Length: 148
Length: 170
Image (cartoon, rainbow over all chains, first blue to last red; front, side, top):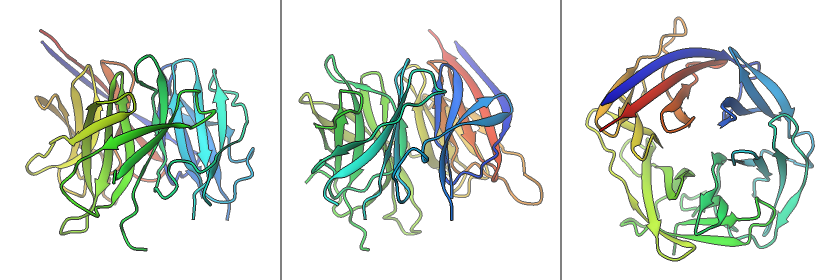
């Protein structure tokens, strides 16, 4: 009937990350770390006991501030998106693609009049959502009520 | 009038022209959601986010489940995970059953993990030294239908990784 098991391992990180972001890829464990003067967006991997910086995606960008991050892990493919924090009317982002977790391939895109014009967003990892024979990745946002 | 809104892509992020509508017919007006994120597994869409419209100004997790109407329009609904003497934290699923994370109080001296609201495990993080180590920010990182990690940073630099196996039969 019931089987429950618990183990504890420790990991140290070179980088004191402002925000951690965890994903499993090929049963390896990967992190998207964020330090912050000076800033980076490091793609890291746990080989046992320590994280290992594999990429800096911030470098390959014309990106002025701190972006929202939307990561998506299909089984074979990893797709990450760095989206500039508003505040125009359309939103630009830079995406990175791998099928291997080591070598991420640059790019840049723009969504004009994008649907989330006045929505607040925050970074997250996710999976494709099957909706009648189609896979969709979602970027979702919330209405701004608190006075600013 | 929909408080939550998703733009969506079926071309693996090339274009974001698709629009997914989220009717969360909630009772309250003008309530700010924080740190919203969709929890997705197989067919099911759900959302995990915070609200702070309570006495203490402390933020509080809400988790809403959604089912389907149109090909792009979902209908969501709050899921009760309230639990006396504990505070709702993170949410995941092992094998079409919820696994749920809780703190003892809002200061996460301890974290309890509940399986299908039916069995539970206690996580008492060890101290980093002279200062208290909590499990603030503990989240789930799912591996497959029997295994998930529960990670949190006791203090800066230090990553506490709980490897968890669970299986319920019959």
